[PDB]
Amino acid sequence: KIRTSPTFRRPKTLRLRRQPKYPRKSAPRRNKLDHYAIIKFPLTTESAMKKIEDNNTLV
RNA sequence: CGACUCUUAGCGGUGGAUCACUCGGCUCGUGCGUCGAUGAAGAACGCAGCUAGCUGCGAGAAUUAAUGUGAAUUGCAGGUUGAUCAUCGACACUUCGAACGCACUUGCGGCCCCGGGUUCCUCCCGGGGCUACGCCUGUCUGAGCGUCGCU
Ligand SMILES: [Mg+2]
Ligand SMILES: [Mg+2]
Ligand SMILES: [Mg+2]
Ligand SMILES: [Mg+2]
Ligand SMILES: [Mg+2]
Image 1 (cartoon, rainbow, N blue to C red):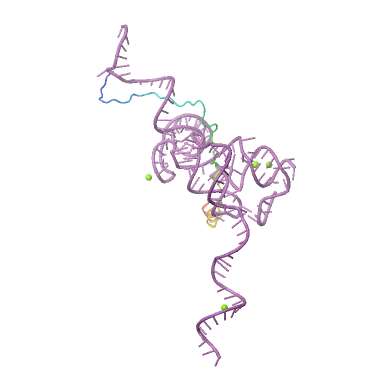
Image 2: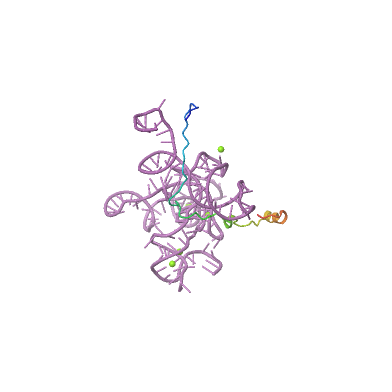
């Protein structure tokens, strides 16, 4: 071939993709942060009740 | 006289000594002599109907399963096919931390696979699995006017 540049760079190298012979974890972790765990409980204070009454919103 | 002061005694205060108790120490001896990338020691934050501390525990959060035991736990409520305790082999085990995508603000990514938008056509949202350094054996892809062999 021809060398038109004075510098030497590391040649392009083919690299494989991970192909494990066994998953490291037996099962995926259950999603502990779900919709039931998102909401804990509503608020019942004076400001919350007024906010529900007028602003059409929940707390 | 009366006040004040002093002494002694009774009683009452003040104080917490002495004595008697002791689920604590100290010392000696005996058997065993076991941590961690399958993530340790340590730290942080959370978890109880009423819970601050101590203790216990980890979003399955003062505990799940299993076994033994056999009618309680208790401060107040409430509700034998096994209550409560103990054992502990199944399961689970938040964030940091050797701490591991990059940094330490919990900020910013990349790749692959799923569920929402789509009805993959790409974005966007959610979920899951990987993405640290060094090193060993093997595999693949390479480099060298290094040593050569055929053209
Ligand atoms: Mg006196
Ligand atoms: Mg608490
Ligand atoms: Mg049980
Ligand atoms: Mg039982
Ligand atoms: Mg900064």
